[PDB]
Figure 1 (tube, protein in one colour):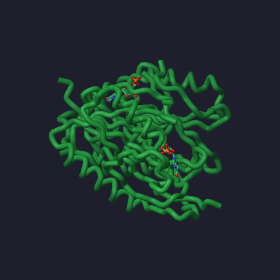
Figure 2 (cartoon, rainbow over the protein chains, first blue to last red):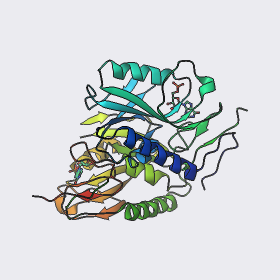
Figure 3 (cartoon, each protein chain N blue to C red):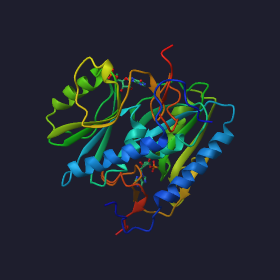
Figure 4 (cartoon, each protein chain N blue to C red):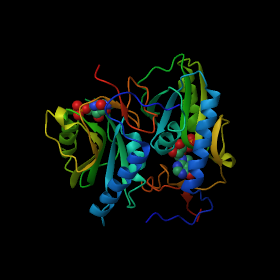
Length: 164
Length: 164
Ligand SMILES: O=c1[nH]cnc2c1ncn2[C@@H]1O[C@H](COP(=O)(O)O)[C@@H](O)[C@H]1O
Ligand SMILES: O=c1[nH]cnc2c1ncn2[C@@H]1O[C@H](COP(=O)(O)O)[C@@H](O)[C@H]1O
């Protein structure tokens, strides 16, 4: 009974699957000979993370963190590691900006960002996104891990509501 | 370059996909008219969780917890909710046993368990598993979210090593 909202942004499970596989392939190529450490930003990015890692045929480690201050700390060391932050959607960029400064403080070998979506018209602070799934217009999206008042994270596709 | 180990347990991505879809269907049927709250036990169950929820066409909420004592607490209320714990693999059952007592203490409306795997020959404490993916022989498995010294969680299939 998965039903799309009536918003302007709509991305099918098929379109998402293909893009994620493409991103995984790019990462595998860019990180050949390396062992990246992917950090999933909970809760929204967990499905993107699950699909993305399965498309990266390289030896790698993972960790999970919650941010909003951080509600969940890192468990594995990141110093000297080639880190890849996995985000759901970059809106104003404030959260990612804070996260990047936090991670850089531990002196990782490098840090790149993978994000399923980005709403650049809302950007308040410039943050990098090396692996972007889709650039979209300003709209509240949900599904594929992203919530609407805690619900709808289970929709296999990305949908949205009207600003109304 | 995803390569299987030489252990006795081997489960393909295809076999896993079909089983997870079956489990999701059962849950959707069993919980018709309800709004379950699925709690993913990190880190191992995150991929099973990602695939499972996308196979449950019902309105539902989610949360994530880390256990080993708990390393990550619950954020959403569970009192009066129909809770479904999502685990990666039940070995001795000690962890799940502790988790169930913890959750029951908050008086949820009900609690059921979904687990991808179970090694019953290792069971030290009897714990319920209402939605089980596969019952397997005693072996150390990895892949599909489960790690081998933090690595191999990204394998799209379940594999194993030899006890040797
Ligand atoms: O359109 C949306 N749908 C769902 N969540 C969103 C949306 N926009 C922003 N968020 C959440 O806000 C968090 C940080 O947003 P930011 O700090 O403004 O870039 C993201 O990681 C999302 O969890
Ligand atoms: O064969 C295995 N492979 C990977 N992890 C395992 C295996 N067996 C047990 N575990 C981990 O041990 C945790 C709890 O095991 P238990 O308390 O003995 O039932 C599970 O949630 C897994 O994360």
